[PDB]
Image 1 (cartoon, rainbow, N blue to C red):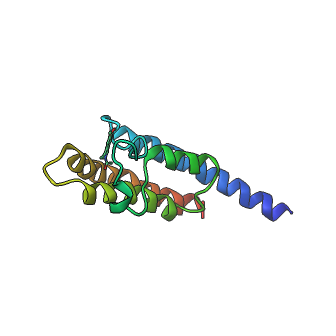
Image 2 (spheres, helix red, strand yellow):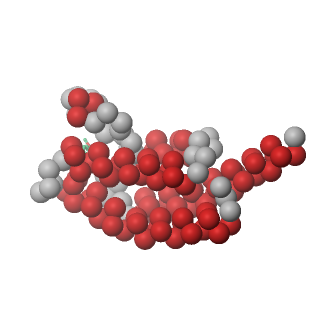
Length: 123
Ligand SMILES: COc1cc2c(cc1OC)CN(C(C)=O)CC2
């Protein structure tokens, strides 16, 4: 149907905006602490601690398969990256501190992304 096509154009547009958001967020991680899944070879007990792992590579895979239906679902995954890290690692670690900085700097980006999604009506 034409309606289904229109929907898919909207999803494609959202995906384009979210790709830009994701790039901007990952720039705020120059250490690449959050670029890849935490390795279960180097951290074998990780899944005992964290029930829903997330990282930028995994987000990007879902993104390019148009797997985010709205900004909220994307934000959920971003929050998982930050929140998992702040649980697993202690406050005095480079990991925890990197998560705080990512959260603080990313909020700026996400604040405007929400306005843009609403404004352009991508949902
Ligand atoms: C072995 O290598 C790494 C280990 C970890 C991280 C990053 C790494 O390399 C980039 C990040 N971490 C998080 C997000 O909890 C702690 C574990």
